[PDB]
Image 1 (cartoon, rainbow over the protein chains, first blue to last red):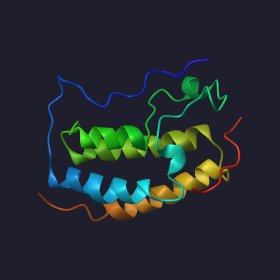
Image 2: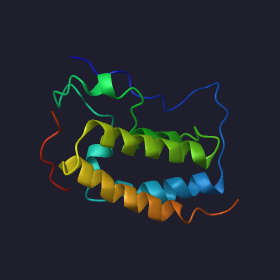
Image 3: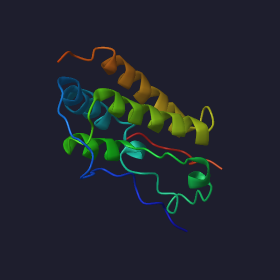
Image 4: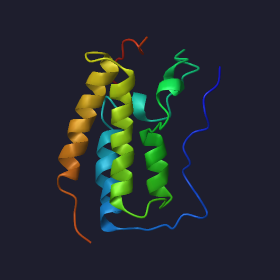
Length: 126
Length: 9
């Protein structure tokens, strides 16, 4: 069984930027989610081999995880905050597509998502 | 199937 290659975290053709919102996304938003007790299943790409989930990458064609997001932010991969926010939303959406309500991974995602939304409700200015 | 039981860190 095989995992796909992970999402790219660097691209030498993609214009890079640092914005105050992107800085906040790394130093406030990602930091707070990463240290949460429910973060661990979301800190790296889903390992469908180890979890024996052979349908995971049949169902989820746009995978995303906080390890990828962390690296993208550290690399200045993004041009704007909305690109990064979309990656978080993709991560949560994928979880809700694949898994069922009341599964532990879903309860964990829901709590992380509430925290995410609380922090992005106060995005700073440039 | 799903991912099973997950304990908090």
